Length: 83
Image (cartoon, rainbow, N blue to C red; front, side, top):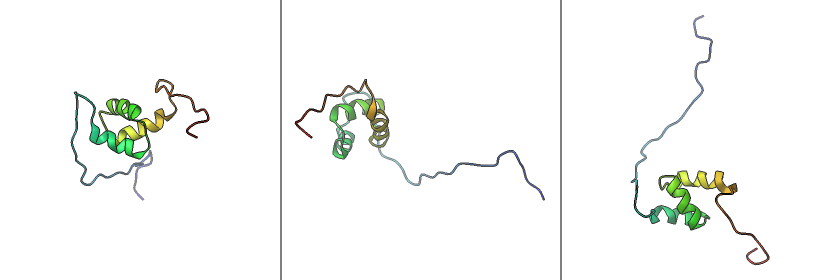
């Protein structure tokens, strides 16, 4: 018998082939926005979020999810119309 005791491991991940292109400064990215706006998010948010997510299509998503229920986000009301 031979082994440690205090912990050992508890993590697993992998990222085979994962490269695109980043866009910093200047107006927001549309290519990315499209993705979001294509999913089911408002340009405003997507845009804002993006800017906060270094213009990330995936990242933003989460931010959009987490912020999905954020006040700052500022959202209108939902009357009768558009149900």
